[PDB]
Amino acid sequence: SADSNTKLCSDILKYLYMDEYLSEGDKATFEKKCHNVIGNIRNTFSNKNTIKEGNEFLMSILHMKSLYGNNNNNESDVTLKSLYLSLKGSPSDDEINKTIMNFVKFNKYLLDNSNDIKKVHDF
Image (cartoon, rainbow, N blue to C red; front, side):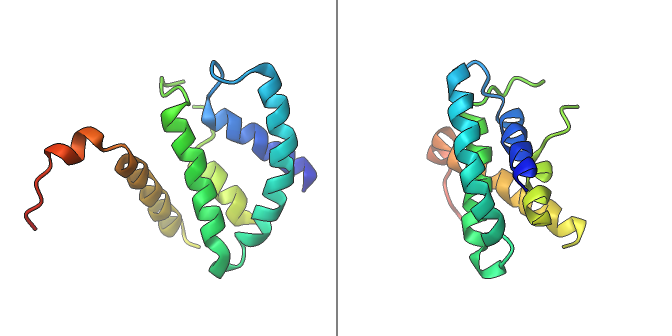
């Protein structure tokens, strides 16, 4: 598990792609702390009542990619579905596909300063 703990913290930073924004010491402060957290998060993400903790954390990985991560494209074999199935390893493919599409539309929902102002609601 601790080996898999070292897998994810590399896999998260490979997904974040924040390489110009973090320091070399920041990655050192990163790998120590996410080694502590994820071992708890894998426990809570299993019991399906307590899934809101992992639902925010997997959202928080995606949201840091949009703001600080370089969205210049650079396949790379690491997506949300790499990260989600690693935690969910601790459902059919469609439901996994839907929850990530739920996560993608929520990140677009958070960044609608230009969108929502021009929008006029007429349902």
